[PDB]
Image (cartoon, helix red, strand yellow):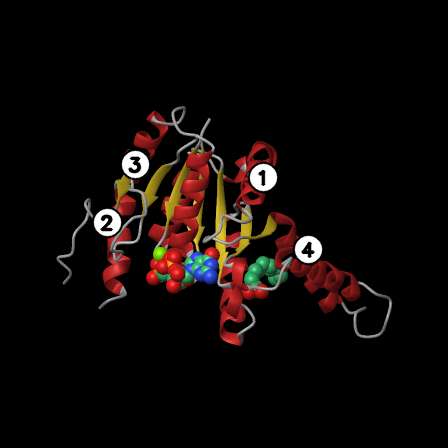
């Protein structure tokens, strides 16, 4: 009866600080999580990882990105053993929390990445937490990278996703709600009986937009203050009981 949260986001989005704050927030509710760290390159792991990749695999590399890639590969093979371990502890802990490496491509597009994700998907309800670097979200490369990576995950993983606009302590108040409002009011503008929107193309886009948006939820949080983490867990819990109905179809073993 345990559920899994997998933290993904570009370098600097604050995913390790986010996971620390999630841990601490969950500890506060007297429900500590099982923690898994899949970044080989990190110095510390906030509280302690119950399963940590690096004391399982040390390099002994034979560049700096392939060196991260390969580590994942090695890990992804003992995956069934890992799942056995977490399954044995599935009624002791309420949540399992997974940190991923900053080099995001190495996990989202890779096949050993997709295996780890699916192996978890097929054994527990699991939600993707997609951490976004909000105070620079509007920078064009960051926006494009985030749209492209996020949609790729939704597509290839076919898992529920919470978009986490992180670091709201230095961003526009009510950021997450105003983001959804502009996105939804955008979908609507798209659907109008005016010239420029009637085409089969614009109709295909509108559909594609709705299919992506409907899988995900949006929250803003500050990992520093713990502001927003209640709401985050609400979303997680929301996506969890829904998991039986919608997502279990796409994950067996
Ligand atoms: N203002 C503010 N800053 C934050 C917050 N969370 C993280 N940061 C800052 O963002 C920077 C990156 O934090 P870190 O958690 O290491 O990001 P990361 O994405 O895990 C780095 P890597 O991808 O290499 O693992 C740090 O300087 C950290 O202090 C937040 O909630 N508010
Ligand atoms: C293709 C439309 C649906 C995709 C919505 C989720 C993508 C979230 C990307 C975050 C963008 C941001 O930085 O403002
Ligand atoms: Mg990190």
Residue 147 point in image, percent of width and height: 55, 64
Q: Residues within 10 Å of mark 3 (few under 14, many from 20)?
A: some
CA distance for labels 3 and 2: 12 Å
Q: In the rendered image, which residue does mark 4 sit on?
A: 210
CA distance for labels 1 and 4: 22 Å
Question: In the figure, residue 202 lies in which quadrant?
Answer: bottom right
CA distance for labels 3 and 4: 36 Å
Q: Secondary structure at mark 2?
A: helix
Question: What residue is drawn where x is 79% and y is 74%?
Answer: 196
Q: In the rendered image, which residue does mark 3 sit on?
A: 82
Question: What residue is drawn where x is 39% and y is 40%?
Answer: 119
Question: What residue is drawn where x is 34% and y is 32%?
Answer: 86
Query: In this rendering, which labeled residue sits more in front, label 1 or label 4?
Result: 1
Rendering quadrant holding ligand 2: bottom right
Q: In the rendered image, which residue does mark 1 sit on?
A: 234
Front-lying residue, 42 or 244: 42
Q: Earlier in the sequence, mark 3 or mark 1?
A: 3
CA distance for labels 2 and 1: 35 Å
Q: Secondary structure at mark 3?
A: helix
**Callout 2: CB less than 8 Å from ligand 1:** no
Q: Residues within 10 Å of mark 4 (few under 14, many from 20)?
A: few
Front-lying residue, 80 or 238: 238
Front-lying residue, 184 or 21: 21
Query: In this rendering, which labeled residue sits more in front, label 2 or label 1?
Result: 1
Q: Is residue 15 left or right of residue 146?
A: left
Q: Secondary structure at mark 1?
A: helix
Residue 75 point in image, percent of width and height: 26, 46
Which label is found at residue 74? 2
Q: Earlier in the sequence, mark 2 or mark 4?
A: 2
CA distance for labels 3 and 1: 27 Å
């Amino acid at each position: 009866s345990l559920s899994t949260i997998i933290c993904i986001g570009m370098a600097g989005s604050g995913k390790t600080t986010f996971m620390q704050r999630l841990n601490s927030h969950l500890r506060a509710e007297k429900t500590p999580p099982y923690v898994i760290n899949l970044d080989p390159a990190v110095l510390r792991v906030p509280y302690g990882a119950n399963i940590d990749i690096r004391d399982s695999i040390k390099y002994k590399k034979v560049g700096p990105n392939g060196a991260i890639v390969t580590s994942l590969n090695l890990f992804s093979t003992k995956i069934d053993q890992v799942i056995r371990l977490v399954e044995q502890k599935k009624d002791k802990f309420q949540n399992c929390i997974i940190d991923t490496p900053g080099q995001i491509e190495c996990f989202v597009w890779s096949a050993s990445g997709a295996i780890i994700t699916e192996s978890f998907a097929s054994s527990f309800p699991t939600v993707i937490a997609y951490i976004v670097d909000t105070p620079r979200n509007s920078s064009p490369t960051t926006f494009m990278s985030n749209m492209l990576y996020a949609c790729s995950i939704l597509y290839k993983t076919k898992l529920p996703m919470i978009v986490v606009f992180n670091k709201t302590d230095v961003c526009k108040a009510d950021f997450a709600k105003e983001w959804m409002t502009d996105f939804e009011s955008f979908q609507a503008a798209i659907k109008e009986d005016q010239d420029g929107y009637m085409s089969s193309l614009v109709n295909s886009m509108s559909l594609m937009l709705e299919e992506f948006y409907s899988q995900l939820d949006v929250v803003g949080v500050s990992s520093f203050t713990g502001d927003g983490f209640d709401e985050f867990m609400q979303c997680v819990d929301k996506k969890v009981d829904e998991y039986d109905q919608y997502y279990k179809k796409h994950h067996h073993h």
